[PDB]
Length: 503
Image (tube, rainbow, N blue to C red; front, top):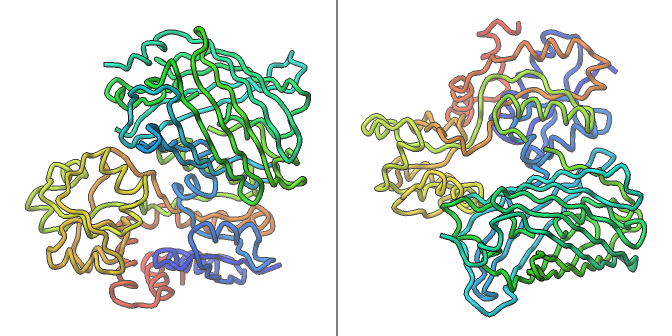
């Protein structure tokens, strides 16, 4: 009609910029603006925008480039996090796979993995690290059988060779055999190819030898030889998979498909002759017969993405358009990433500036960080290992305890959002993520295409905010609300008036 709904989550910075977006539409169009709060994280704005203003959703909100990448869109193949499992003399891994659905939604596959050597001898038990994988799925146009051509590059990261590894120094032939059952539908897959572990490359073709595969091929990818991962030179003592060779290892997985069935898989990976063989039993239970898996509603290809500002922005732009029909406008100008802050007296005293400069100082206490930040694998833990932070202690303070401790110098470093209003009232300086651990979180306005169709002027109106809010500005405005207790709606107005952007 004549009404547009602007959403915000229950977060000070979001409330300010969403008030700004609403004021701009009111100042530069004749539309009615409905300002709608959502409770949750930035995924609730996304479900609200998919509903739309017509259905007690929203039409517009401010999203962060990195947020659209990591959740909402998601890495299709994230890092497979590996940890030692003393009790099985092996390793454990947990990770999520994201399968695109033909209707635009995403189908999550939670993988829980365990590996145990088949032989009795010593094997490598690694420190925590991860595997980075990119799979490309293709078709052989001449192949009549239900099949899948697969290319995989796998590298270990997150941190002179076992006898087992000596068996991988060239190209190794691979045989994969799977016997399967899903809700009673029995099937078999056979695959052959080769693996080149020095390059972390797998090349394989899989065929269903019992007819039409009853599940989509992308759900079998993780099931159908992590011993071909490329472990860099400085990490070769963390490669359990090759060190268990030639006797090999048993791999077991539970794969739960969100709101659908689960896969139970047991595999033996070992040398036979000079072939690396992966023999799998898979059982699938409790799948909905009209669901994504048994209904064959998943897209065949994984996507590829980029973690630099422009590539991330362009990626969320393309995919949000292709899936769900949603338009990204221009960035407001600030990057609200997660960061570390110290007292500004401490920063000039020791001439700090960057995370590396901080890491060089081990006589510091980082117990002022939130538990979530200390517990997330890509929170402090990953950061600690990329920068080798040598912090004295690491207690986990939440509420506002963190801020009051750095105030009294019980703690010297805290975690914070880069635009956190409280950084100014406590006189702390943020530090530069020089090694770019975190993805960029540039805020930009987001709008449904059909609202844009109905009201084309909204594109120009919302782009009048492009690069109109620097990091320092968003900090000062967050401060006025969280520090001084001003109404966020009045804070947004005053800023826009002072810029001549509204009446």
